[PDB]
Length: 46
Length: 34
Length: 47
Length: 316
Image (tube, rainbow over all chains, first blue to last red; front, side):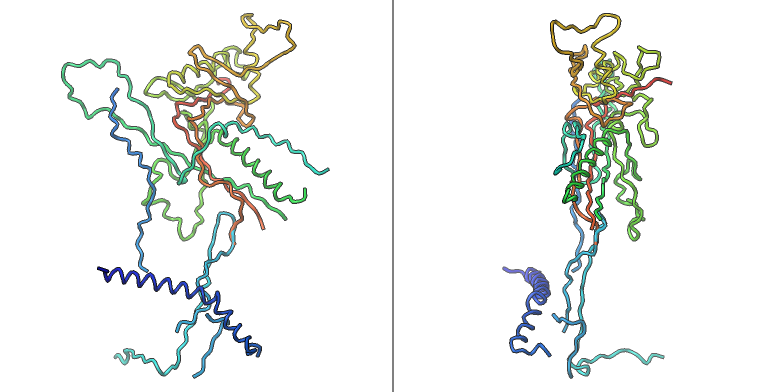
């Protein structure tokens, strides 16, 4: 008996949560992980 | 004498906030090839 | 795609005592794969 | 030498005798005026035919809270903590001096504190319309009878409460000297006790400035010869008084406080006075290297005709 309005509210909440989580995690981890992988093969120093 | 005790109304309540709602790169410049 | 530089990142500017302030550092950028891949049409040629 | 000497006069009896109570708004209010009069005769002829009663409900009283900054500026070793504690003691002394002053709360709002409709509409956008919050003092809440702009008048007695005729604020009249000496009469505090008993305050404390204790000290003696000390082979010269009992049977304990105005005396009571606080003393800094303190405090009084004040001067 799950309502579609409940699912829409859940979708909205989850979308905003994912947006915030991405905005954080990007600069928290991936901005460093990319350059770390680049240094792994020595491709960052140009 | 003359006890009514019907007009206390010492509510002293505060507001409730019932407002309404209507709701990574590193460098400064980025480029792509086409 | 929406190229973001820094999330809002709640932050403060300074403090003069009780005169609090706050700042945001939202920064983004837009890119398009091919300019000649997304079409647009306007209304013109009036009069 | 590895220490410093500091006098640190920190009596502060009033602050510890009145307690404190937290609030959640910069403006608090209570409501209590009196009980209904006696009306004397209340005979009847077997019929009511009333007029919707003469209830005349209570009046709503309020008070405002002020701000104290006492900034710290650094340009003994660690002098920071030393100056911080010194400024803390200084702000406590300033609070003890203010709360017993004759200030009167002054602000754009007088009796329509709410004005949620207007509430100073020309405030947002410019934020430079800042007025100065001034709280109510002791002599203002004790059933005053006027105020010289922002200070209570020290030459006018207070009004009478409708419940029972009582004047809890009176201009002292030292009928002993021909208006030359500025001192309490021998029977001027007993008049206050009588008035309080008539109004039913139950106060039992009296704060006094050391510039007046000599009066109560000499009160134990006289010149007519009806009051005199004795010493039956006693190696003591006790010259002090710390308790009084009016003919009505009301005890009164005396305490001395140097932070009171010389031209006044107060009749306090523990529960009848309470210290309302909104912002506790916080060590912090301004917006985005100085330190500062900020303490939001206000004064509350259960009922004006409970506590008593008495001004000392000559009539003119």
